[PDB]
Amino acid sequence: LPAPDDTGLQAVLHTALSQGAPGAMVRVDDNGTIHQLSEGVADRATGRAITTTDRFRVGSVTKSFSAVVLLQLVDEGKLDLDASVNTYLPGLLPDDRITVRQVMSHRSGLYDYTNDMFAQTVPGFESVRNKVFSYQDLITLSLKHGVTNAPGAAYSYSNTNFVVAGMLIEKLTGHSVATEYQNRIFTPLNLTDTFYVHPDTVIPGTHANGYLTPDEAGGALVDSTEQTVSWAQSAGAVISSTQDLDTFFSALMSGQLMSAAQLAQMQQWTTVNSTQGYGLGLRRRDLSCGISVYGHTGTVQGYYTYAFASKDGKRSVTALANTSNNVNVLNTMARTLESAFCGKP
Ligand SMILES: CC1(C)S[C@@H]2[C@H](NC(=O)CCCC[C@H](NC(=O)C[NH3+])C(=O)[O-])C(=O)N2[C@H]1C(=O)[O-]
Image (cartoon, helix red, strand yellow):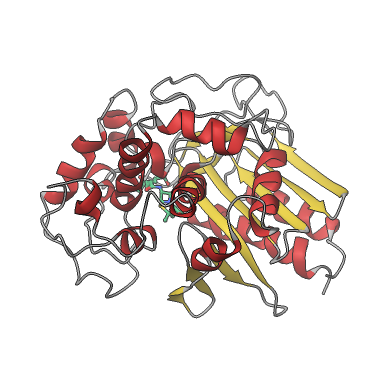
């Protein structure tokens, strides 16, 4: 690969701050040589600086953790990707036709209940931040709406899919998702900054605070750091660090977390758009210089995450901005992948 471009990474972070991120940071693990940059503040009220060791909420990056657990269950003979969801969770869905593979790739047609919750950004956050939901509560909220398409038909993102994934993990293992993440992923990879504490609202240890951008332009930011994330759970509640998400996606792509057969299934791409695909709890992004990278993005209130690795896991990058509901910031932070993988123009 080309050399990572630290001047370009520095410019991306400075642009994100100019667009409303209180703080922004990035860590690259380039085959054993570390790159680490940060600019701005973890806490905008106290002024404490952000750093690449600050813990944060990874949002839908959590789905890659859920998918790894489910694909290990396929390796163990406990789960068949082409069986019906209802085979394992009787009576759950009105269509006994929807399969596990379809949920894991966002091809199920299940309505995304969070489009009801967050029609208004700050009111919807204030509504859910201190609520505790069961998995079944969230499925019932989805099923108030009919499906949006035929099973298998189209990519349509829905958090409901990885609520189903959490329910499958707990049903088939007899354990909580926190126990399965710890035993199958966090402990074997020594992810000392990585946690699943739901429904606790505290982020353990030194962390970046999250700042939710209101829908009104120029409105005051809302501290969204402490919430249950119970509206997402196995779709979005993991806490981690840049070093630990680099370790995780490098281990995944280098073949340490499942059989070769299941990794191959995880990388069967469904088209998202002309430069992106979706596998099984895994995203592919095609970069300008002809390189593809693999991993996941996350959005949870106050935190935007990108965490991607090269095909062989030898270069990994994790970037974090501690704001959300700011599409300019989101789009700017994607440029860290260009600078880290494609290097200087
Ligand atoms: C598909 C995504 C982008 S959204 C999905 C999941 N996060 C959510 O579903 C939260 C949606 C509300 C986010 C909120 N926005 C609003 O409230 C809008 N009114 C904000 O910006 O904080 C996550 O994480 N995924 C990202 C993913 O996979 O990258």
